[PDB]
């Protein structure tokens, strides 16, 4: 801010004067601008400043003079070169401008000789020019390359400068400008000769300033030149001798740094001239090397970068020569071998890698000449020290152990014994690296990726059983370390919760995936073992405790919840779907992972038209099998794989051949039953969503197996309409369903099939009107347009049959369902128009911040009113029958779906309805009709898809028989009023068997169980009904027995008989006679499933009598 | 053009109540006439929601409190909310979640005190945030006239919002 | 239980046979090394698994009572080192024929394994381990332990390089020492007692865990009476015995509760309490080391608990324990200062932990009266650093905390006061008179821990005395250090704002001097650390300045002295002025920073600073300055401000000309 102001003062004031008024300025426009840290804020401030600054100094001293301007321009150029590296890039046209300015400034310095500002200036300008390696322009490179070559090919300048020459000449030579790279590279010979033949006789001792440049030059241009053979060994080698002294002067180590760096980026022919010096200079080369390695320098890594490189030359020519050229090699590397032993005495530290990498280079090749378990067996033992000791807190950076492991890999690139003892050790080293793979940088992450593909390559080449146990345990470690879950959207979080509820899990798969599809080939048998091994292990994994865990904690933590009063409600809930908690959070923690990635693993790996018949035939059977214990995500891995297998034609064609290797397809058919049943019966709406992705897709694949049978897609799409747009998950899977099957032999059946079809379709179009959401809708539109024929007469009978115009408005709006008396003027209160709206409010779930709270609290209050103005002799009184029932139904269902969003709110709404179900027992009938009648249809809700409303309901009843049994008001009211007791059981048994027995069965059983604790104690009333308890089974048993359409029913009914156990406490003594006669009469009338019950009663009742 | 804000409830409230207290006539019926003089100008939907909040409020402010048979006072406190602490991010989502909690606390506060006493249910959704780190005799008089004027606004407001 | 007994009773009968062949092969045996290596490391492995399935049955006696095993444990103990660290977790039998063997074929291992190198380092339980773990993770276990390194990796994962390898040699080597024999406790003692080393942590955890886990009323007393008699009479240096005390207490203070035998023999160690031997330096060391050790463990033996279950006082244990700290009148000499006063403190400070559980008002007070020391101060008064640093070597804070705790826990139930002297004289409180000494600082930190929960008008005049001592004394801790100034001065300021009603009996009577000089000082400094460190420095004193302003002694003369800084090329104007804005905050802008008390146109010198610099301090100072000068001058006599209005007018002119914009 002040930077613009100040620079606009002393730049234009600099246009007429100078001196102090420069430096202060430049310190100012420096320091504040300097401290600029984060981008955006600090960046946007600094952009304008720097720009006006560059240009300003440019034309400023460009159009001024000397006296003191030169000093100011000097300073600004200094502060600028330190502004560029900091201010990342984003200064490109500005940059090229600055650079041509810098050469202009040395130019103005040409007239005047001697002095010192020429040096400050000159050097600084140079550094501006140097820190320019963004490039990628065009003429921006030749514009400076040409003219620096121009000013360099002729100038007899002394020394205080010559570093720049070769600095630049290499810098531009590293770009590309073709014929420049040529002319330069040839012209360098001159300078090389000047400085080298200079360093032999003209000066006794080396000179740092021109070595600086010279070696920078020959380092930087030769990567582009190549074919070096002669000049490098002399020049470089010498520089090594020259730093093998040192005294006090700074930059001494960098003199050493520039050549060794040269040599490493020249590892080709140059390193060959060093190969020749593996005898006279076998000590010399690695002694300047290692002696550097020990010096406490900023270029420690110069030591390796030269070392590692010339070791590449060792293994190089070592292998590309003959046998004559072997022993003089073994000399050097055995000195390394001594670096492996004597590090026990003196910790080589950094050099400990060297020798590992040492017992890497030659051991890749000289191994071949002679047996060498010595090496590698020692290395091996060492790597087992350095990893097992990671039971020390040495942050032995897990980038270190794959330097060691890299080296271990080519160390391992050879084997031929198998002496046990190597099996365990190599094995664990594998697993360690396979566990060191999350923690890296991304770069080194690819390094170790490369490691594991290598070391595995060797193990595959070798021993034919081990590698398998490798893959298993190494997969175990990954999937168990998974914890915690990296999936903490609604529907997916819901399935993962329906499973289990509460180093990333995700990360590791990059390594596994990328390993199997890295460098191609050999990835074959590799990736196959990898797959199946991973499987069989997981197969037994969840098979550990998870399998138990569901059916366990669902009856365990529920027991810790279970008390005398809550056990009934819990029985009610065992009918919708389980508690969903799990017991065994270990198998229950890793196995979620196991599927969960296992998609992201199996989707991108071995998927060719050769692997994808064996994939299906095999992988199908044991999976679905292992699902036969019921678990969403367990199923979620089956259709992902099954439909991802690009075999919609061989599988379809085969299946058709079976209807008009087959055993797998016999399973294909087999799952459909248990499958659809699982959706409808047990599957809670969120977990229902889960299973339904997975029951949509298999059909989607066996197209011809989706012949008839509409109960599938109807529940499918029908959820996949306005429920699953919240995440294009359930929705998506459906378009493809229709499209694929829209012409897959579904042509013969349409007028009867497609009304169901548009029938759903309407709530993905005709709601979404009320993979972006709108795009889903568009795909709908396309999907329908392609048809034309019968999109109409379907959604006709659809919309009409669904009515949707159900207009209650209580006895056709006589007057006011609930007046009020507040303003005492223009009351408008009535409410008859104010009901079906509030109904839609409990269904809203939209603006749950505004809607739920005051919409619901409102409906509640409105409820209060209608509750009250129902006492006199107006319309309200004999008005309760429409009024009260028609809302009342939606009152408990309010408390249930309120559970999901109301919380404290729903809490108080619950007892509110409960007081409302006690009331008209502790008062009178007419209003008895209501609750008892609707909720009497709530256990019809359960035999619908409806789920938790049923539990809520049972919790109502259990309290309404409590409010009869509390409402004594003389048992004269007992007989006179006919809402409970006798009247109850009539409604109940008749309820047990109304519809033969189907969507009403799961109602009766709940009732008996929900009332049991009360049936236990209440005098002779405990008597008659116990006999009618015997019809109950006779009821429910046979009821479901014949129409055993899977459990849900079959179970709760037996539980009602486990309420028939209560009778067995010897009483009234006519039980011993009549009640015992019945179980006798039950074998000759053994009704298909009463069997287990019949016999039970026989032994049990002959038992105490 | 200001009577409906783009978002900030506090501009809208302070504006609305500058329209309401003195400009709107003290008469009930005369306000019923001033209404459609003021509605058509917005040329912009949900006006009638604004209608209701002006009128239900004006006719209900204090014949209704003690002769029954909160969202304007929590409205003014929700105009001193944005005039002080809290700006943006999910912190304002705990202020819209606490706005949910209190908007329920209007006509619920009665019923939840019925359940037990004055302080119960107050935290509501924030009670979970706090947890992680005279009952029958109480229900009976709320259902009578305990504070049925608190039922008036939750009506109006629940209608205003959608 | 079946296949377990299968695998072992055979494994003894063959553990006799084709094992030792390979062993002696190795120990006697280029082909020779490979044969040795395979054969041995194999047999090692086998022994590993074999003792593992030994331990879930009638082992231990089946371990150490059958045949041909110990030898095998020890032979491969005497060949190598690395492929030996894993065959080293197992073992530890008892009874003779073995005890000798272990100590022998062992110490010698630590030799080839354990140097005195510099610091670097990085039925019940078994039934817990089997019946507690599940199956899902177990199968990671069973597939991890048979051979391979998931044997011992599974129970670990969930100078530098070799000192690290040695380090893990200690890892196994004391790691398994956590759960076993007694000599196995003994060597660790020795080792802890060399110097200090990031072995520290591992030793603490190890020892603590020994005491907690073992619990067996037998083994328990064994480790105790054991390391005791490892402090029995015997020629050892000095560290080895102090470190013997530290890692013995930490062997005990976190241990099983049945003290039995240690507490028993406590008859004998009381009997060794008294002695003398002057001197020959020797029994000097051994006196101020032996003599000061037992008292040390003894006193938090009476740490807590079964004390009231002892109901005792040892009648006479008070005698020496209270005598000796009060005492040593003797002059220094004989090197008996900082090597005996250091652990001469423990007698008192820790013996108190035998007063609190015998404390019920007056006699406690008299345990805290009357003076005579200055045990551990003077010693370390010439040393020490911060609060915690004042705490440890002194080990007087570290007790006087819990002391002030049970002492206020016994000051409040009888009653409570609001008068200063009537609590002083009855209770310890009488020591809160400060003094002329070097042990003021510690006593001051004890007050740093009183004021938390003590206060109020009580310790009154001392607060102001503690404003008087920090001159010489505060400067004597070099200067203080950042956290030094804060703790000392910041706390005295802290407690002083902590009240209203009573800083007025120091605001009407005592402030006149003590405050004045203090604030003088506080300002003069506070500018210094801020023009050195960070901004908040001024504020860290300013605010309290404000808490104090409601009286003071008008020290604004020097406040404008400090303003009246130099000229440009030094940002000291700021240093001077921010004070001045601080000033202006209150109190008729503090008499208008004395602008006409010392000189007559200092005020004019303020104007004279701002006009010269646009600086971010001179403007705001001028700003508010003219503010309250203008609000007061519109509500007080106008003639006072008018000259200023003229001066600023002059400024505005100069600023328009001298530079346009800025």
Image (tube, rainbow, N blue to C red):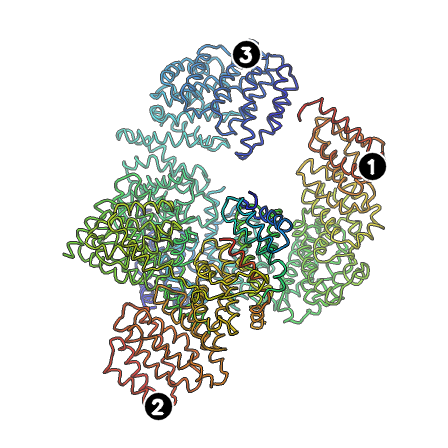
Q: Secondary structure at mark 1?
A: loop
User: In the image, A749: left or right of C322?
Assistant: left
Quarter holding residue B29? bottom right
Instruction: In this rendered view, identify the residue nearer to me: A931 or A142.
Output: A931
Residue A678 can be seen in this image: yes
Q: In this rendering, is residue C164 above or below A96?
A: below
Label 2 sits on residue: A1070
Please, which chain is the residue tagged with disc 1 on?
A: C
Q: Secondary structure at mark 2?
A: helix
As measured in the structure, the alpha-carbon distance from the residue carrying label 2 to the one carrying label 1 is: 113 Å
User: In the image, A332: left or right of C341?
Assistant: left
Quarter holding residue C532? top right
Label 1 sits on residue: C594
The N terminus of chain A appears in which quarter of the rendering?
top right
Label 3 sits on residue: A108
Of the image marks 3 and 2, the number of the one nearer the N terminus: 3
């Amino acid at each position: 801010c002040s930077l613009l102001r100040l620079q606009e003062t002393l730049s234009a004031a600099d246009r007429c004067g100078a001196a102090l008024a420069g430096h202060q300025l430049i310190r100012g426009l420096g320091q504040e601008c300097v401290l600029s840290s984060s981008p955006a804020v600090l960046a946007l401030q600094t952009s304008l400043v720097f720009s006006r600054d560059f240009g300003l100094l440019v034309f400023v001293r460009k159009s001024l003079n000397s006296i003191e301007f030169r000093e100011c321009r000097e300073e600004i150029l200094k502060f600028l070169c330190i502004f560029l590296e900091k201010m990342g890039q984003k200064i490109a046209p500005y940059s090229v401008e600055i650079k041509n300015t810098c050469t202009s400034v040395y130019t103005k310095d040409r007239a005047a000789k001697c002095k010192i500002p020429a040096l400050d200036l000159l050097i600084k300008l140079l550094q501006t020019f140097r820190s320019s390696r963004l490039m990628d322009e065009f003429k921006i490179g030749e514009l400076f390359s040409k003219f620096y070559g121009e000013l360099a090919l002729k100038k007899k300048i002394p020394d205080t400068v010559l570093e720049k020459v070769y600095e630049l000449l290499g810098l531009l030579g590293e770009v590309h400008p073709s014929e420049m790279i040529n002319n330069a590279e040839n012209l360098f010979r001159a300078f090389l000769g000047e400085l080298k033949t200079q360093m032999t006789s003209a000066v006794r001792e080396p000179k740092l300033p021109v070595l600086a440049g010279c070696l920078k030059g020959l380092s930087s241009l030769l990567c582009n030149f190549t074919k070096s053979m002669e000049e490098d060994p002399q020049t470089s080698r010498e520089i090594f001798n020259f730093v093998l002294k040192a005294i006090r002067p700074q930059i001494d180590l960098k003199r050493y740094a520039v050549p060794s760096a040269g040599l490493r980026l020249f590892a080709l022919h140059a390193s060959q001239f060093s190969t020749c010096l593996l005898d006279n200079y076998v000590s010399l080369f690695e002694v300047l090397l290692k002696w550097c390695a020990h010096t406490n320098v900023e270029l420690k890594k110069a030591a390796l970068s030269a070392l590692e490189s010339f070791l590449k030359q060792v293994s190089n020519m070592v292998a590309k020569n003959a046998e004559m050229h072997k022993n003089k090699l073994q000399y050097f590397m055995e000195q390394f071998y001594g670096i492996i032993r004597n590090v026990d005495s003196n910790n080589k530290e950094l050099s400990i890698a060297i020798r590992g990498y040492g017992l890497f280079a030659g051991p890749c090749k000289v191994i071949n000449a002679k047996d060498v378990d010595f090496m590698y067996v020692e290395l091996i033992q060492r790597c087992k020290q350095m990893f097992l000791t990671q039971t020390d807190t040495g942050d032995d950076r897990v980038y270190q152990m794959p330097s060691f492991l890299q080296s271990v890999a080519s160390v391992l690139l050879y084997l031929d014994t198998v002496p046990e003892v190597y099996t365990p050790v190599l094995e664990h080293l594998v697993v360690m690296q396979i566990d060191s793979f999350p923690q890296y940088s991304p770069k080194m992450q690819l390094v170790c990726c490369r490691a594991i593909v290598k070391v595995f390559l060797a193990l595959a080449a070798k021993g034919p059983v081990l590698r398998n146990c490798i893959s298993t345990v190494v997969h175990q470690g990954l999937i168990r370390i998974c914890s915690k879950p990296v999936v903490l959207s609604e529907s997916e979080d819901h399935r993962a919760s329906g499973e289990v509820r509460t180093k990333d899990y995700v990360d590791l798969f990059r390594h596994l995936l990328s390993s199997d599809q890295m460098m191609d080939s050999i990835l074959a048998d590799e990736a196959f073992f990898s797959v199946n091994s991973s499987s069989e292990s997981l197969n037994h994994l969840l098979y550990d405790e998870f399998v138990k865990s569901v059916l366990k904690i669902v009856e365990k933590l529920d027991l810790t919840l279970e008390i005398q009063t809550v056990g009934e409600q819990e029985n009610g809930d065992e009918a919708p779907g389980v508690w969903m908690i799990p017991t065994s959070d270990p198998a229950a923690n890793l196995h979620p992972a196991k599927p969960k990635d296992f998609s992201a693993f199996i989707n991108l790996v071995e998927f060719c038209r050769e692997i994808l018949p064996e994939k299906q035939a095999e992988f199908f059977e044991p999976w679905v099998y292992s699902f036969s214990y019921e678990l969403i995500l367990q199923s979620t891995r089956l259709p992902l794989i099954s439909g991802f297998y690009k075999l919609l034609s061989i599988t379809v064609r085969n299946a058709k051949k079976i209807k008009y290797k087959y055993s797998c397809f016999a399973l294909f058919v087999k799952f459909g039953k248990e499958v659809a049943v699982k959706m409808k019966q047990y599957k809670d709406e969120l977990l229902a969503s889960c299973l339904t992705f997975l029951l949509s897709l298999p059909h989607n694949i066996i197209e011809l197996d989706v012949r008839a049978y509409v109960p599938a897609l109807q529940m499918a799409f029908k959820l996949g309409l306005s429920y699953t747009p919240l995440a294009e998950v359930g929705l998506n899977a459906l378009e493809e369903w229709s499209i694929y099957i829209d012409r897959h032999v579904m042509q013969p059946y349409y007028k009867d099939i497609l009304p169901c079809l548009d029938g759903y379709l309407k709530t993905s179009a005709l709601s979404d009107e009320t993979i972006s959401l709108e795009e889903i809708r568009i795909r709908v539109v396309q999907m329908l347009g392609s048809l034309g024929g019968q999109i109409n007469k379907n959604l006709l009978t659809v919309t009409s049959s669904d009515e949707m115009m159900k207009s209650y408005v209580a006895w056709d709006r006589e007057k006011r369902l609930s007046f009020a008396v507040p303003f005492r003027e223009m009351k408008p209160v009535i409410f008859l128009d104010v009901f079906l709206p509030r109904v839609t409010e409990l269904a809203l779930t939209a603006s749950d911040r505004q809607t739920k709270v005051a919409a619901c609290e409102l409906l509640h209050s409105m409820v209060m009113f209608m509750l009250g103005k129902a006492t006199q002799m107006p319309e309200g009184g004999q008005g309760a029958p429409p009024m009260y029932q028609l809302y009342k139904r939606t009152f408990p269902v309010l408390l249930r779906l309120a559970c999901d969003v109301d919380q404290v709110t729903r809490q108080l709404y619950e007892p509110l309805v409960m007081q409302l179900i006690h009331w008209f027992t502790n008062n009178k009938k007419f209003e008895s009709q209501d609750t008892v009648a609707l909720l009497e249809a709530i256990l019809d809700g359960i035999v619908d898809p409806v789920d938790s409303t049923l539990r809520d309901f049972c919790g109502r009843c259990i309290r309404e028989f409590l409010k009869w049994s509390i409402k004594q008001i003389t048992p004269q009211q007992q007989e006179k009023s006919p809402v409970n007791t006798k009247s109850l059981f009539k409604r109940l048994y008749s309820l047990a068997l109304h519809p033969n027995a189907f969507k009403r069965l799961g109602a009766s059983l709940a009732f008996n169980n929900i009332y049991r604790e009360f049936r236990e104690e209440e005098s002779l009333v405990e008597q008659f009904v116990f006999e009618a308890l015997v019809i109950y089974m006779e009821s429910l048993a046979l009821a479901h027995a014949d129409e055993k359409s899977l459990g849900t029913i079959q179970q709760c009914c037996d539980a009602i008989d486990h309420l028939c156990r209560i009778i067995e406490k010897k009483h009234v003594s006519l039980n011993k006679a009549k009640k015992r006669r019945l179980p006798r009469g039950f074998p000759p009338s053994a009704s298909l499933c009463l069997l287990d019950l019949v016999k039970w009663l026989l032994a049990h009742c002959g038992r105490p009598q | 053009q200001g009577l409906i804000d783009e978002n900030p409830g506090l501009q809208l409230i302070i504006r609305n109540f500058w329209s309401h207290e003195t400009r709107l006539p003290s008469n009930t019926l005369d306000r019923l006439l001033a209404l459609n003089s003021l509605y058509s100008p917005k040329i912009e939907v949900h006006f009638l929601s604004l209608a209701t909040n002006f009128l239900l409020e004006m006719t209900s402010m204090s014949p209704d409190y003690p002769n029954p048979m909160x969202x304007x006072x929590x409205x003014x406190x929700x105009x001193x909310x944005x005039x002080x602490x809290x700006x943006x991010x999910x912190x304002x989502x705990x202020x819209x979640x606490x706005x949910x909690x209190x908007x329920x606390x209007x006509x619920x506060x009665x019923x939840x005190x019925x359940x037990x006493x004055x302080x119960x249910x107050x935290x509501x959704x924030x009670x979970x945030x706090x947890x992680x780190x005279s009952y029958r005799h109480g229900d009976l008089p709320d259902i009578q006239i305990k504070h049925s004027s608190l039922i008036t606004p939750l009506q109006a407001v629940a209608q205003r919002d959608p | 239980d079946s296949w377990w007994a299968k695998d072992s009773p055979l494994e003894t009968k063959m553990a006799v046979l084709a094992l030792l062949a390979k062993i002696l092969q190795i120990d006697s045996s280029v082909f020779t090394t490979y044969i040795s290596l395979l054969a041995d490391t194999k047999l090692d492995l086998h022994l590993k698994g074999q003792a593992v399935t030994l331990l879930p049955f009638f082992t231990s006696l089946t371990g150490g009572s059958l045949e041909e095993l110990r030898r095998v444990l020890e032979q491969l103990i005497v060949a190598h080192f690395p492929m030996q660290s894993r065959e080293f977790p197992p073992g530890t039998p008892r009874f003779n024929n073995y005890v000798d063997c272990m100590k022998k074929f062992l110490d010698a291992l630590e030799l080839s394994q354990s140097p005195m190198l510099l610091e670097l380092m990085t039925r019940r339980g078994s039934c817990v381990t089997q019946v507690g773990l599940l199956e899902s993770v177990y199968e990671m276990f069973r597939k991890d332990d048979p051979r391979l390194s998931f044997t011992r990796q599974s129970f670990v994962d969930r100078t530098k390089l070799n000192e690290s390898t040695f380090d893990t040699q200690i890892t196994k080597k004391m790691g398994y020492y956590k759960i076993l024999d007694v000599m196995y406790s003994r060597l660790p003692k020795d080792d802890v007692h060399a110097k200090e080393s990031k072995i520290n942590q591992v030793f603490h955890g190890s020892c603590i865990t020994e005491g907690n886990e073992l619990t067996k009323t037998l083994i328990k007393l064994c480790y105790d009476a054991f390391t005791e008699n490892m402090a029995g009479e015997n020629q050892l240096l000095e560290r080895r015995r102090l470190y013997h005390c530290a890692a013995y207490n930490c062997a005990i203070s976190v241990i099983c509760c049945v003290f039995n035998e240690l507490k028993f023999y406590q008859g004998f160690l009381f009997s060794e309490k008294p002695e003398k031997n002057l001197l020959i330096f020797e029994n000097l060391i051994d006196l101020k080391r032996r003599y000061n050790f037992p008292v040390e463990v003894e006193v938090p033996m009476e740490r807590k608990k079964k004390y009231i279950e002892i109901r005792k006082e040892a009648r006479e244990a008070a005698n020496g324990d209270s005598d000796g700290p009060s005492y040593m009148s003797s002059l220094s000499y004989l090197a008996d200062s900082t090597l005996s006063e250091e652990m001469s403190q423990f007698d008192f400070s820790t013996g108190v932990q035998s007063y609190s559980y015998s404390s019920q008002d007056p006699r406690p007070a008299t345990g805290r009266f009357r003076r005579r020391e200055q045990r551990d101060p003077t010693v370390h008064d010439d040393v020490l650093e911060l609060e915690m640093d004042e705490l440890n070597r002194h080990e007087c804070m570290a007790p006087l905390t819990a002391l002030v705790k049970h002492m206020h826990r016994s000051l409040g139930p009888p009653q409570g006061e609001e008068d200063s002297v009537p609590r002083d004289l009855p209770s310890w409180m009488k020591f809160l008179h400060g003094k002329l000494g070097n042990p003021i600082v510690p006593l001051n930190i004890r007050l740093f821990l009183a004021k938390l929960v003590i206060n109020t008008e009580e310790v009154f005049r001392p607060y102001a005395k503690h404003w008087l001592s920090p001159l010489l004394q505060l400067a004597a801790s070099e200067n203080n250090g950042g956290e030094g100034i804060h703790y000392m001065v910041v706390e005295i300021v802290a407690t002083i704002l902590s009240w209203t009603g009573l800083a007025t009996p120091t605001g009407v009577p005592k402030d006149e001097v003590l405050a004045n000089r203090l604030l003088n000082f506080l300002m003069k400094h506070v500018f210094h650390p801020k023009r050195a460190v960070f901004r908040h420095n001024l504020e860290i004193i300013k605010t309290l300045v404000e808490c104090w302003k409601d009286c003071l002694s008008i020290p604004y003369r020097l406040i404008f002295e400090k303003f009246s800084g130099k000229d440009p090329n030094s940002k000291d104007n700021s240093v001077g002025i921010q004070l001045l804005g601080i000033v202006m905050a209150n109190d008729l802008p503090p008499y208008d920073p004395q602008c006409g008390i010392q000189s007559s146109e200092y005020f004019q010198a303020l104007v004279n600073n701002m006009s010269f610099v646009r600086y971010k301090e001179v403007y705001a100072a001028a700003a508010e300055v003219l503010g309250l000068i203008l609000r007061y001058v519109m509500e007080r006599k106008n003639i006072l401000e008018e000259s200023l209005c003229e001066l600023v007018a002059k400024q505005l002119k100069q600023h328009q000309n001298t530079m346009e914009d800025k």
